[PDB]
Amino acid sequence: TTPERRVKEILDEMDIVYFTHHVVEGWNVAFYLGKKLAIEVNGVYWASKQKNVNKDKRKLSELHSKGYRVLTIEDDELNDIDKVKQQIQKFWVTHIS
Amino acid sequence: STTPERRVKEILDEMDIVYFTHHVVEGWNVAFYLGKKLAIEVNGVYWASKQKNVNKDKRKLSELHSKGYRVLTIEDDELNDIDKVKQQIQKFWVTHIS
């Protein structure tokens, strides 16, 4: 139904464990996979989305500066799950291994 | 800047309400399960990845109800007026949990 729900289902299929809506360095991420690996879900727009480019930008720069690798999945990309699974795959394999 | 589910979570945290996230009750997946057969769902008119299938929503609610479950559905757009969603959740909680 929701982007997060869809990402969760992919993670379960790949048998990947995670903390949901987990706080890291004062920031919120959709899924935390450990070893400073996080997945975020975003999109150009949704009804209750309050735009803030500077905040979103700062968030990534701080996390990255602290050793975090963040994979941001766009809600549109979900209509092509085969590509999303690929992004999650590469992300997990190249960073956890 | 935050997903609808994230925004609902923050509300629950503020009200000091505990939950299972993306929980499955009677074969149906809910965004937040609060126990005592209480759940909160997050939906909306339509978004980027949403596939319209009301025949699964009309079924979900009707079946859960007969099993004793009570589901509060929050539309993504409702979050723009956060106070309205807080009072819904507050009343929902007090109603079935008193």
Image: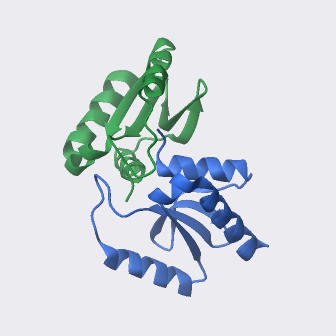
Chain colours: A green, B blue
Task: Identify which residue is drawn at 48% across, 83% down.
Answer: B63
Residue furthest toward the front? B81
- Compared with B32, B97 (above or below) is below
> Where is residue A35 drawn, in percent x and y?
49, 24
Q: What quarter of the picture does the N terminus of chain A occupy? A: bottom left
Q: Is residue A7 visible?
A: yes
Q: How many marks?
A: 0
Q: In screen coordinates, is A61 left or right of B89? A: left
> Where is residue B21 drawn, in percent x and y?
55, 54
Q: Quadrant of residue A86?
A: top left
Q: What quarter of the picture does the C terminus of chain A occupy? A: top left
Task: Identify which residue is drawn at 45% across, 70% down.
Answer: B28
> Where is residue B74 drawn, in percent x and y?
52, 63
- Compared with B8, B58 (above or below) is below
Task: Identify which residue is drawn at 44% across, 77% down.
Answer: B60
Q: Nearer the viewer, residue B28 or A54?
A: A54
- Compared with B69, A26 (above or below) is above
Residue furthest toward the bottom? B66
Q: Is residue A97 visible?
A: no
Q: In screen coordinates, is A54 left or right of B89? A: left
